[PDB]
Length: 143
Length: 143
Image (cartoon, each protein chain N blue to C red):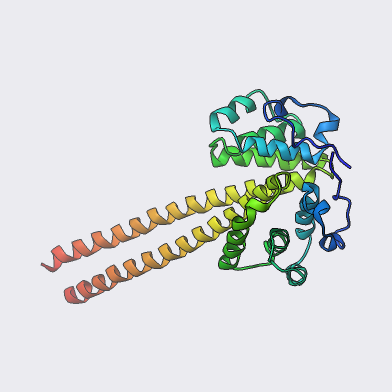
């Protein structure tokens, strides 16, 4: 039987500290639910009130900044830092972190696929332009 | 305070039924953790005994089949059915479903992006071919 931190207000959830809250999966579940309700300007403001010296603050910061319109390099650094400290996460919290990490990894894969698409778009047009110029040369020669 | 079903054995988590278990987010969190441990053949063997009649069985079935190597149309049908039933999910469970649904929506977007990429690959080769044929026909006539 665990404590229920879900009814905790989203305005006060980012102020709770201690081992009692940081080992409860229902607390971390509430932080993700509360961060999903915030706008990018509020998420970054709450993230500025946190550091990343330990796994607790790094998890809070990553949860807040995930939807704060960050760049793919910024999301990759957040995931990499948490993956290095994920061994310190208690076992009861890890299922929450694993689901959150899988979503962030899918966002990184999505951004990587967007970049591959634009690279193909530019590669295709560059190859099409070369054949076009060769066609214009032959057409002018025939004319 | 909420009951803790995280230490519940993964071999017996699929047989748990009732309103006391299905309204506890820790039960559904353990369900996702246990399904992540199963191979596609084991996930399908558990999910084949269930259907999508209600939100409880549809969620259990979708959690098991998420990593069972299903097709994008099959995952879309599971997500769409659960979205229609998401109104009946209790408030304390919805944070578990929302993060699970967001991960499934990212998999659908990743599948659509990959299909769009191969679509560009075929359209690019088709246009390149058409220019190559035009160039060749121009060369023979130039000769």
